[PDB]
Image (cartoon, rainbow, N blue to C red; front, top):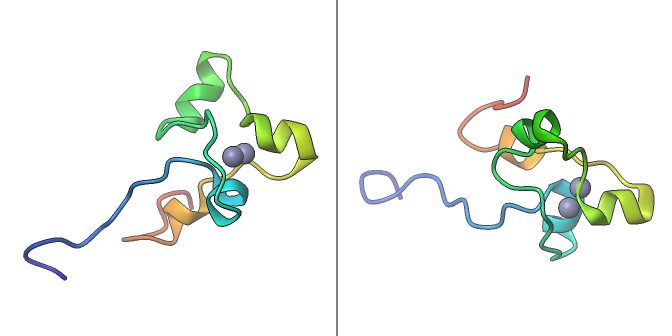
Length: 65
Ligand SMILES: [Zn+2]
Ligand SMILES: [Zn+2]
């Protein structure tokens, strides 16, 4: 798990959904989505959770630090 492959990103769903096995609108560019008009996936806006890519931040490095 290094030369062949290191990172295994598949689900793009934000922290709360990916954990709860929910797929949301939140793309890989959820931040860039905020700039476009987006802000939080329907899940977060529905349950009032926390749209974050912390999962992304805990991968190869603190992507969002
Ligand atoms: Zn979500
Ligand atoms: Zn969310």
